[PDB]
């Protein structure tokens, strides 16, 4: 509900910001702005993934297909967001090392500053919106869009700082009067420009950006891929679980024990406990049920393989 | 085993091909070749993902964590490959529309042809290797690397055809003598080149490439995401399953019925069948077991909620 409205307003803000970029590019006569807009378009994919995930979360119904109900949509959306972000991070690192080998010059720092502060305020507003998720499946999914919004805001920060760096240290004697640049490899050749060391600042800070993005994304992907692999949660303990279950009176062993986490706090477990008398079984059944209860798990299915 | 050796030899061939590209770039004095090599590096990610998936497939052991055993590693690898490929396809489409708006000229068609036929033969060899997967989990994972190798070979085909197109229709009067190009937007300005319509061939065929890649990838991702969501397989029928189970003598109803697919042909099912006499339960248990047997499922766990 409220998270749905948050996603909707954030997506609307992204599209309005794209419209703003194309409108300011109409005035600047620049194709690089079109490139930046088309590359920032990639947030719409993650936003619509989170949207459809939240839409399918409210299914919680047993059907003729997927008799559990579409409860794992949240986890699937989180995993999709994590993998997509890692791929985008790889691509950004590739472009960064390319530009680091070839230091392309900067263009239009004032309007880049304007649009960068615009994106700064917008992305900080979006981050303040997505900070209550830094039951559980909701935060599990929203962590992906939080990571993407953090990447957005950090790109805004880095581009604004680079803009001011050029503004404050690049006299850039390159056009109009007698003006060349010694640090450019080949400016379409057949005084020298200002201090050129700032040229590599964009890649040498984009590398830090992608570093922090990987370092912060890895936990979300780890948790999600662990949940989807049918692994035991961190809370319960098999070693003492089976020991207590055996120590229960009436039981003699356990053939097969299975525990996993469906989507969230509700986890399921099955067993093959064995008794000796069929006359009294419901008492030991209630006993095993309350053992599981006191040990976390509440969705139980135990089969008395008699003798 | 043999699939492991296939992955190993293919990865070795990719690295040898990267070495070949850097060696021929040392001779050509071209950074675009470095860009192409660094972009073709992305296949190593998918190959190592498939590698670690195949390495974890052979676990099949009950442990203190993930009591089922790491059997879903195959499906997880397939899903990772599918999502990664879709993200890369998005990036390629973005670069393609950018180059379609700005038709950058072509460089060094002869050596591009040489390396393109090299990549052609290598990728066709790799495809012939990965054609037995066009139990089930093996093919399910290998479909990802098959899709990536198809993308590789199709990129080789498209670049070779574009190379011959330039070779056979681009006299390109652009350098040396009196030579300009009317179709270039601004060749760093303050006869005209040959027929320029071929300039857009690279994007207008890369779009077909990404179209066919999406159209062929979607089934793999669909199947994988359906398996990981705990959905009923396509084989069995709940509507008649529950009906027969009720028609069984002794049973009176079924509280909760759950069916899902663990990783492959081995699927699991649980139930809550209810009887009336605890004196005789093993007979109806064997009956329900053989009903499930004749109806597919073999991993069973049924609990007699008595009265
Ligand atoms: C979906 O990922 C985004 O869209 C983000 C993050 C959200 C943002 C802040 C809206 C935009 C962009 C963000 C950005 O700032 C704009 C560019 C870039 C093209 C700009 C230029 C200049 N000058 C450049 O030359 C290089 C150095 C090649 C930049 C490369 C990195 C890139 C795409 C990044 C940092 C990526 C992440
Ligand atoms: C991991 O995806 C790959 O690596 C593949 C497929 C495997 C291949 C065939 C080894 C290489 C590459 C393949 C390729 O051919 C080389 C380039 C490209 C940079 C070349 C140029 C020229 N000229 C260009 O200007 C544009 C038009 C921008 C091309 C863009 C597309 C791209 C990267 C593609 C088709 C991507 C897929």
Image (cartoon, coloured by chain):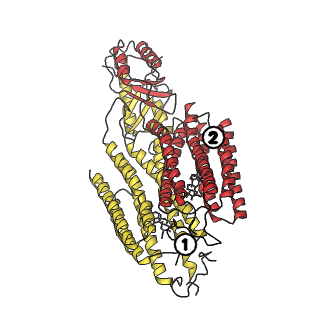
Chain colours: A yellow, B red
Label 1 Cα neighbours within 10 Å, binned few <14 / some 14-19 / many ≥20: few
Task: Return the chain for callout 2.
Answer: B
Where residue B246 sits, quadrant-wise, is top left
The residue at 43%/70% (across/down) is A30
| Horizontal arrangement in the rendering, residue A43 relative to residue B52 (left or right) | left
The residue at 47%/57% (across/down) is B97
Res. A248 in view: yes
B267 in relation to B206, above or below? above
Task: Tell me if the residue at label 2 has its CB under 8 Å from ligand 2.
Answer: no
Label 2 Cα neighbours within 10 Å, binned few <14 / some 14-19 / many ≥20: many
Image spot of residue A64 (x, y percent):
35, 29
A28 in relation to B78, above or below? below
> Which residue is nearer to you in this view: B103 or A237?
B103
| Horizontal arrangement in the rendering, residue B167 relative to residue A41 (left or right) | right
Kindly check if marks 1 and 2 are in contact, taking CB atoms under 8 A apart as contact. Answer: no
Image spot of residue A190 (x, y percent):
64, 77
> Which element carries disc 2, helix, strand or loop?
helix
| Horizontal arrangement in the rendering, residue A278 relative to residue A58 (left or right) | right
Res. A250 in view: no
Where residue B234 sits, quadrant-wise, is top left
The numbered disc on residue A104 is: 1
Write down which quadrant ligand 2 falls in: bottom right
Task: Tell me if the residue at label 1 has its CB under 8 Å from ligand 1.
Answer: yes
The residue at 62%/38% (across/down) is B130
Residue tagged 2:
B127
> Which element carries disc 1, helix, strand or loop?
loop
Task: Return the chain for callout 1.
Answer: A
């Amino acid at each position: 509900g409220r998270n749905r409205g948050r996603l909707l307003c954030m997506l609307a803000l992204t599209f309005m910001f794209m419209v703003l970029e194309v409108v300011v590019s109409r005035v600047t006569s620049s194709l690089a702005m079109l490139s930046d807009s088309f590359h920032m378009l990639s947030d719409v994919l993650a936003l619509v993934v989170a949207l459809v995930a939240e839409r399918f979360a409210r299914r919680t119904h047993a059907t003729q297909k997927n008799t559990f109900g579409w409860i794992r949509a949240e986890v699937m959306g989180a995993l999709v967001n994590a993998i997509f972000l890692t791929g985008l991070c790889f691509a950004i690192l590739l472009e960064a090392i390319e530009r680091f080998i070839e230091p392309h010059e900067m263009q239009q720092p004032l309007v880049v500053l304007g649009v960068g502060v615009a994106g700064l305020l917008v992305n900080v507003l979006g981050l303040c919106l997505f900070h209550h998720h830094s039951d559980r499946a909701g935060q599990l999914n929203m962590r992906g869009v939080f990571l993407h919004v953090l990447g957005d805001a950090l790109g805004s920060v880095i581009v604004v700082v680079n803009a001011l760096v050029f503004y404050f240290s690049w006299k850039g004697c390159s056009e109009g009067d007698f003006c060349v640049n010694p640090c450019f490899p080949d400016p379409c050749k057949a005084y020298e420009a200002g201090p050129c060391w700032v040229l590599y600042l964009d890649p040498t800070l984009c590398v830090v950006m992608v570093c922090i993005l990987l370092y912060t994304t890895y936990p979300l992907l780890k948790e999600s891929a662990l949940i989807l692999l049918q692994t035991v949660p961190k809370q319960i303990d098999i070693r003492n679980l089976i020991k207590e279950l055996r120590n229960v009176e009436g039981v003699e062993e356990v053939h097969e024990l299975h525990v996993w986490q469906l989507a969230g706090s509700r986890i399921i477990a099955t067993a093959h406990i064995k008794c000796e008398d069929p006359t009294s079984y419901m008492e030991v059944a209630k006993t095993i049920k309350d053992v599981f209860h006191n040990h976390g798990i509440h969705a139980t299915t135990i089969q008395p393989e008699f003798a």
